[PDB]
Amino acid sequence: NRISWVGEAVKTDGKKSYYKKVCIDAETLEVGDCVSVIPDDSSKPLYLARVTALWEDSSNGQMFHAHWFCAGTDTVLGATSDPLELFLVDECEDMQLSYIHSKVKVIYKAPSENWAMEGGMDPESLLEGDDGKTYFYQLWYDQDYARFESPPKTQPTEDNKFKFCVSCARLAEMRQKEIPRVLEQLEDLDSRVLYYSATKNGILYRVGDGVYLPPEAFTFNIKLSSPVKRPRKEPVDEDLYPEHYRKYSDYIKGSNLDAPEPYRIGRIKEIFCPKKSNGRPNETDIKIRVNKFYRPENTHKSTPASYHADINLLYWSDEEAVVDFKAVQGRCTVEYGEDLPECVQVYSMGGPNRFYFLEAYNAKSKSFEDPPNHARKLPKLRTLDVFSGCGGLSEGFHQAGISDTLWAIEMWDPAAQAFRLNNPGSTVFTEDCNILLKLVMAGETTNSRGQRLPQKGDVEMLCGGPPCQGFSGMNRFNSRTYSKFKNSLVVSFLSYCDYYRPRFFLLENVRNFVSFKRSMVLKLTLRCLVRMGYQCTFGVLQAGQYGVAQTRRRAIILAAAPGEKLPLFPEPLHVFAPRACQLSVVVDDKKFVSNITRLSSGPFRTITVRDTMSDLPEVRNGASALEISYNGEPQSWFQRQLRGAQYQPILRDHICKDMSALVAARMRHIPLAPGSDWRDLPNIEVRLSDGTMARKLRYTHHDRKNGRSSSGALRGVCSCVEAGKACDPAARQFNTLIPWCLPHTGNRHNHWAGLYGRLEWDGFFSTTVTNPEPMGKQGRVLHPEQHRVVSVRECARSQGFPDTYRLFGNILDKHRQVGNAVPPPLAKAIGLEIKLCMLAKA
DNA sequence: GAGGCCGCCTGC
DNA sequence: GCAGGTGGCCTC
Ligand SMILES: CCc1c(C#N)c(SCc2ccc(N(C)S(C)(=O)=O)cc2)nc(N(C)CCNC)c1C#N
Ligand SMILES: [Zn+2]
Ligand SMILES: [Zn+2]
């Protein structure tokens, strides 16, 4: 035979007889030993597990419990992983003892007590270095969220110790945390049992608390007539508008007609369970009775009621609704305004999910004020901000209250000056970050300006966005591009992390950072952090979901030192167009998401172009007055926030690029209706403001793809159309109102949708760029009504900069500073997650 | 400096 | 095939 128990049994739990030791052919096995197990096809490598229990089964025979390790190559790291590094996972199962192939040694590599001083790995060590030739683990891994975290520290029961499986225990904790449950009973009525409290997903709900509910959870009293359908596309003069046919897509870039409704908000009146005919309550079916809260836009006053109202302003209602407890999307605080000790602004700024109501809403009296008697300091982290720009990321972190950016590195001098203007106590370095790091590593204390260099222990948080020029393609690395990456600013920034070993680390970038070079930039970044011993994760965030009227996805890498909690990604605050909120990432055929659970709705309504800039005075093309009058108070909640509490007599930087006479005429001929762009231009001559003329565009070749006009005219302008001929200059066709190059190459660029495009008041900005040009890719830069490009101030508003935030240089310098920044509201959301970790640190 | 001009690749 | 991701040359 081969397998024989060592000793007598220790417990007989039914059909199972547990043992403490077993003997397989020439080895002995005890609880706690590590083993390998062959897979079902010997092509796949060995599985590795820890033995947590051993028992004879009355029917199936000799058994053990395997708590599997995860091979590094099976994580997001893939083949960048240390070949002998394993990761802890909550994966386990009962297994026949006959599946064991060998006993294996696995070492736990704990970070030293002096970990923060052990940095100084060279880039080759960070990128490609491995540990000393044995199986080891340092970190636990979440396979769905791609999170590397310090190993959990669960403790066993006096009855668990002999068979304890930490994976089993943690999975039981998760299941119990996720199943909805009642806790305390309140009163026993004839048909149902009332409760004072319930819990769901770790959140405690009591009678009186506010709940978030899906928009589908209940309707309002409103009996309305159905609105009209989409704008009936009436025919147009195709000779006057030869490019209008290119708008057959019916889809409007930057439009909010597809954004979901925000949550329903209710106050728990009743938590109850149906009582069986037999007396006992059915506690698998928990129901909630709420009073409905009206948002302004839910009243007979439609959407326009939202224009001026506070974003968290509600009205009490006495309409009631019964929903399932499992429908609750979260807890929120809804409290009567004129009974809180603080003021409403301090309240709204002091915590998440805070709403207030001053009046009530009688629906079909359509009136206000209905029955009210029912309604009853850590120190900041010293922060180094690399590639800081003018300071949007540092500004959002400061607003979150977690950071003092004491050092910034910004190579472009106008942005460095702007950072200095907003951060007088900061030390701003303009030289190359490699130079600075090499100086520090050589033992220097000051740079060539006499500025004091940060040293180990000074830097507690490190953040930045490193440029990726040279390796921003999607195709795989070769030797040349990989050398560029090894000597890149990304790797320099990682070397900063390795040297200074801050408590928290943030790398922000364009969304496609997660896909560059077949995701190898991302995988190697994570590999470096793991090699340093950091907890770390990655994800994609949409800036609009955190309160700007702009679509701007960013890739985010977060890391936290051993001893810290690894931050979560922030839950979306505002609803936003779903097409702009694709946050998942596929790496090596594995789809990763973040912890974000608000996927289809959120607490606050979407922020619009109207919210963003309806208060700014009209200005002209080329507006250059640096200091003007606002001409009135803020109108929207967003404007109130960005203008701030203190009266501001002067509006700064509401200045616009001075476009040419031809470009100005084009802009003057873009209609104001939503979705308008160059394809709506007329094919006319126009006398320009400099006496010159704008010529009619007329065709030169037959586009077989697009065919001919409504009445025979060719829709082609170039020998290009032949698809096999070359460009002949005989149709260059300069100084045309309808630009020539857009029909020239439009068939391969989605009709150049959005160029010379107008913003719409109800919509959002396209990604705010460093130099707004109507004929650039992000060409939707025209004001909704004025015949001009958006101003520097309007771009700053689109990024969520306070109006008081100072910029520096000429108009193009200021546009670039604004367009390169992280939006402060996005940075603040991230920082508040970091603050949660600072407060939770054991 | 301001505008004209406009590739290659991915996900669906 | 549509929609989108990425700015960034040159030139006049
Ligand atoms: C649609 C407009 C456009 C655009 C646009 N938009 C771009 S962008 C190229 C790009 C990609 C990545 C990076 N990075 C370093 S990175 C870190 O990823 O930002 C920078 C530039 N190229 C275009 N070409 C003609 C290719 C380049 N000429 C040879 C065109 C065009 N027509
Ligand atoms: Zn288990
Ligand atoms: Zn051509």
Image (tube, coloured by chain):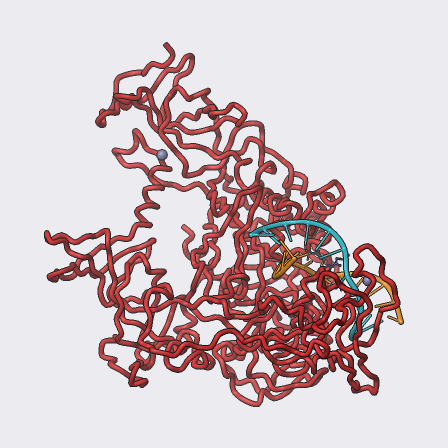
Chain colours: A red, B cyan, C orange
Q: Residue at horizontal 36%, vertical 65%? A: A216
Q: Name the one closer to the observer, A674 or A373.
A: A674
Q: Is residue A525 above or below residue A681?
A: above
Answer left or right for A18 relative to A91.
Answer: left
Query: Percent position (x, y) of residue A464?
Result: 61, 57
Q: Name the one closer to the observer, A661 or A814.
A: A661
User: Quadrant of residue A739 in the image?
Assistant: bottom right
Answer left or right for A811 relative to A589.
Answer: right
Query: Percent position (x, y) of residue A724?
Result: 82, 54
Q: Residue at horizontal 73%, vertical 77%? A: A239
Q: How many marks?
A: 0
Q: Is residue A417 visible?
A: no
Query: Percent position (x, y) of residue B5?
Result: 79, 65
Query: Residue placed farthest to the top in the image?
Result: A1
Q: Name the one closer to the observer, A698 or A54.
A: A698
Answer left or right for A693 relative to A418.
Answer: right
Q: Is residue A288 above or below residue A313?
A: above
Q: Is residue A300 visible?
A: yes
User: Quadrant of residue A715 in the image?
Assistant: bottom right
Q: Name the one closer to the observer, A554 or A397.
A: A554
Query: Percent position (x, y) of residue A787?
Result: 67, 82
Image-quarter location of ligand 3 = bottom right
User: Quadrant of residue A775 in the image?
Assistant: bottom right
| Image quadrant containing the N terminus of chain A | top left
